[PDB]
Image: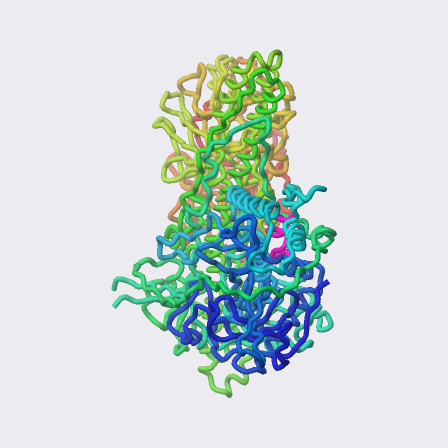
Amino acid sequence: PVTINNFNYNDPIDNNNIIMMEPPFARGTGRYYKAFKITDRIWIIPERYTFGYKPEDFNKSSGIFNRDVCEYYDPDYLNTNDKKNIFLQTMIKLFNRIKSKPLGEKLLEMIINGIPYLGDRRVPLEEFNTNIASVTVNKLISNPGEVERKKGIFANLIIFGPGPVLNENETIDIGIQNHFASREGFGGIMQMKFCPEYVSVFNNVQENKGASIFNRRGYFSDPALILMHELIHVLHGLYGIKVDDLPIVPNEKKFFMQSTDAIQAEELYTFGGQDPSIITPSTDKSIYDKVLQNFRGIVDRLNKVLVCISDPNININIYKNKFKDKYKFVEDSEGKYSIDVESFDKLYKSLMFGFTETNIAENYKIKTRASYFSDSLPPVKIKNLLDNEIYTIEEGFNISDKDMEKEYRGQNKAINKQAYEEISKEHLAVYKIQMCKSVPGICIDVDNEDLFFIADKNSFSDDLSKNERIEYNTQSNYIENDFPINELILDTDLISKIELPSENTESLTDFNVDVPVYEKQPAIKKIFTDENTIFQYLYSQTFPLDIRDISLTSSFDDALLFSNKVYSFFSMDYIKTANKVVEAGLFAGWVKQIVNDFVIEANKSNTMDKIADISLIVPYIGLALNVGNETAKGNFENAFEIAGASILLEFIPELLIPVVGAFLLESYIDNKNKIIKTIDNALTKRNEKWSDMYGLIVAQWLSTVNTQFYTIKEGMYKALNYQAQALEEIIKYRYNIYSEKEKSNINIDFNDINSKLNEGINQAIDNINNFINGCSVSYLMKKMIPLAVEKLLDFDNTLKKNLLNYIDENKLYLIGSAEYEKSKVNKYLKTIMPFDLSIYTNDTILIEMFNKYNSEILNNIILNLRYKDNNLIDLSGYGAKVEVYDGVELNDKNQFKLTSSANSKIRVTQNQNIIFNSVFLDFSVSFWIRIPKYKNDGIQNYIHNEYTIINCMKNNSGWKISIRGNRIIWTLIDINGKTKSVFFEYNIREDISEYINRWFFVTITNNLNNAKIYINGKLESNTDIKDIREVIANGEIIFKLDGDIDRTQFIWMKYFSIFNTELSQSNIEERYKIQSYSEYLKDFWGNPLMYNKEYYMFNAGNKNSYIKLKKDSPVGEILTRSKYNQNSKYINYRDLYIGEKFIIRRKSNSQSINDDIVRKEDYIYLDFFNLNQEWRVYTYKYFKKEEEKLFLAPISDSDEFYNTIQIKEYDEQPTYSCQLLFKKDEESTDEIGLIGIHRFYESGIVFEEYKDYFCISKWYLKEVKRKPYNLKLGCNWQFIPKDEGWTE
């Protein structure tokens, strides 16, 4: 176990556990420091760290030391013995808390026993030298008797108090003659500047700080985790693995980029979590290798060490035993030391991935920031860590007796206010970027922290481009940035049980050492830009403190111009109400109104856009921040549908995607085993190449893209809050304008207001977070992974020949097998590795994002052709090249027509880098189509001639969609030429067909077994496709009528899209209902219903019937449609162009016209033509019966007839039918009835019979309410205009 010593600053010097030490950076001169041995090899010097700092720099100035920290200054901290003692007692309490658990105690035991090797790179392998500043430190024994006698001691860690910046804790290593023993396998005394009271604050971006924008937010850190974080660095330095390699350096070429120091992998390993994933598997291995090479030199020394010249009293065997356990070397029965790969491996992972801030935090149930890369808030002062009511050894701030264990309540700033104190902003300093305009140009100060962190291309290793030699030896190399924290906590032989050498030794005489020199830099950097991006937009949403009367504006430019003007990205109506002034008696009402509006506006963050295959879109992000590519101009939803996530990025990073180095296989003539082994190894190494490539991508996405999206998320949180703050300000102002007398009667509750505004904001934030996370993943998958696959596929091919050629040259030595493997090589380089984020990270948030994304069917769209600027483009996000030739017609209703002309075609060159070739065939194709009726005189050719319409082939393999008369066919052709088809044939002898010349929905799905065809959501045909082998489907897609067609043949299509998976009957039904939806009604053929267009009327309840003005009566009789008269046996139908020709007129124009489209609920006039005149459909106002014959007469205004109709749609399911309702007036809720058909009996002097007439019945009013909706209802009508697709 670990023992924590006790003492008070005032205690006497005993030259043993309380000494006068000469610190390493004192160069053996200057004064000594009273130091206390808190535990073996660990000292505490309760004083400020002054080494390398100028005395005046302890005062706050116009400068800063670190560009990414809100630095707090206080030169008085620790300037009295009582303060020093409080520091001492506090450290003791933190150490006790650390050891209070197995994980922490082990970290301490490891640190205590990880004594620096005796010597560094300069020492001869056969020697131990203690006379160097990294191994020995002196204490002044000098009591009475030769004032100036000094003893040397060994030490592992010396912990000082804070340097100039209290909240800037740092672990420091000793460099000598330009080198660091702590970075070369030796290890060396470690130092640290630490402050337990002023700790960092952080706030979970995805979460919420008690969910209160008006209350304090964020969480304050537990000083014990802060200490353990630094202790982890100590551990690394003590074991000599604090190696340096290719660091993450931020790009700083643009003004919006965040400046900062290079970040070494060791730092990111220490934090843990997702951060390790920012270090590529390549650089992971580099570091791994460097460390191993360091231990190799050390293990060689242990075998050659013979003496210690610096100290005759040092016992060689004791140390060799100690270093053996320390580095986990194994020794044989003779005493020969070597490296055991398994043990080295376990030790390395334990130290780099086991002890991390993340793992420790999770173990101690302490909360911390999500990642190394996240906005750093201002620090706070802990009132009294020494008071067990606030902080305890066992639980820290999260004390259960105070019910502060759950949700880290003890660390929440809005809950545990008795534990901390805000800091005087007067003592804080931050690096700012002053963004100036070319104008005296106006200036805006932005905190470096708020800028986008974008890792520069130079941050990532290019080791993938190097060549690899293959051999019967060659094995895979995977370093898991993970370690089971439980086995570490239960590891029995981990913690050394080998004697710890005495600390006394010869005093140090060689004080040679490099002392770091520090200096502040300007806290403000002025740059010039006339850009108005996120920073200016956020600024335009604030207002000076000396201003209390403001008004909202949608004009960004004015907001920047006037201090009393504040920018708002909310609706025009929201902005007018917010600026509205009212009488005291109407104030309460107004408040309830504008607050409610705020919530409604904020909630538009849950806007859907299913028709464009986008489930979540936050329409106002663009207006709010104008981030990325001018997202504040134009409509944002549209801009997104076109370019996607990419338009939100402030910068498009240049990815590093190297050309994977070539393999060199070692030849083994005669050896049959070695040669086979080689091939297989190359096969596995190739997989290592795919994995490493992916790891390289993930790392870039995390440090160059996801970080940008993080800034955006933060920006939205700030934006929404500014808005709330602005409304609250306006409200306060209006209220306070009134007199006390008036206020007494105004019923207002300001805390409920903030509450409601707040709730609106939280709901908005969760939406925004989902939206933005999805965008991030989208960019990874569609804009990064594909670029990597391209190279990997290339590499593959190059290796394919490389291998077969290899198997060729060695043909003989392989004998009757060169063939067996000739294929073993083909079948392997076939199956390509699917990307899986959980392989490169274990961060729960990131995994969830990925799983969420992969569960949303719409992310399976690999091709989505939509209309834009009179042209079709792929909006799937994979960027397919689309060539639409001159013979193709396109309209803004997403309809495109393929005619019989040669130039009437579309060529689609697909993205070859998408996992489409899943090996077993899994994909769907969907689209709407309108196939014209057959020419009556050309029925023979129609049923005999098959012609292709969409063809996708490559190497005589692929899929095809074709047509033969009334049949639509789906065909597959595998690599071997085997064929399978499935088809849907519709009847051409129906009096009334639902398909001939009518828009209908098609969907073909393909899985390992079947090929299914769905029509309007319903499954229609199936085919077993087991035999079918590999089907190459990523060839060029050609849309064109190909076959022996009639020159009049044409086809209309809409919404053509492809999915790289099998859609379920459920997915299809939904897609069908989504693409069927519209505000307007449709005509018989399925096109928008138009005003001022002749139409024949169809009745769904009486298919074979039609309306005709009765010769003598002002009524419409119902007649039986005429039928196909010719003698073909293949066809039959009822004429559609018969009966009166109606025409829908708009009732009120100015109200909403400027369009000829008929929208549901519109009020219309239903007219028709009686020769050279236009007549109208009327209803006698006074019928008392259930129904009555409609009145058809010239257009006139009779006070006795209703002439206004409201076109309705009562069916909730897709339909081309519509209903016509007669209401008393547009306002009342008095329904007269619906237009339909009724049967009347007529008994005359000569004729006795039944006749149907064009009527209005109230009976329908209740029937249309039933469910499912009765399509056979006689009140269901459809309008039929003449159409080239239908001739009779």
Q: Residue furthest left?
A: 439
Examine the rendered structure and indicate whether residue 663 appears above or below residue 219. Answer: above
Measured as percent of width and height from the top left, residue 21 is found at: 55, 72
Q: Is residue 349 magenta?
A: yes
**Left or right of residue 412, residue 547 in this image:** left
Front one among 1097 and 1055: 1055
Front one among 697 and 1021: 697
Front one among 395 and 86: 86
Q: Main secondary structure of the magenta part?
A: helix
Among the 4 quarters of the image, the one containing residue 232: bottom right
Residue depicted at x 41% and y 27%: 907
Among the 4 quarters of the image, the one containing residue 19: bottom right
Measured as percent of width and height from the top left, residue 1126 is found at: 51, 15
Specify whether residue 965 is in view: no
Q: How is the image coloured?
A: rainbow
Specify whether residue 7 is in view: yes
Examine the rendered structure and indicate whether residue 365 appears above or below residue 485. Answer: below
Measured as percent of width and height from the top left, residue 838 is found at: 60, 44
Residue depicted at x 63% and y 50%: 327
Examine the rendered structure and indicate whether residue 406 appears above or below residue 470. Answer: below
Q: How many marks?
A: 0
Q: Is residue 114 magenta?
A: no
Measured as percent of width and height from the top left, residue 972 is found at: 56, 21
**Left or right of residue 634, residue 1253 in this image:** right
| Quarter containing the N terminus | bottom right
Examine the rendered structure and indicate whether residue 534 appears above or below residue 158. Answer: above
Which range of residues does the magenta coloring cover? 347-359
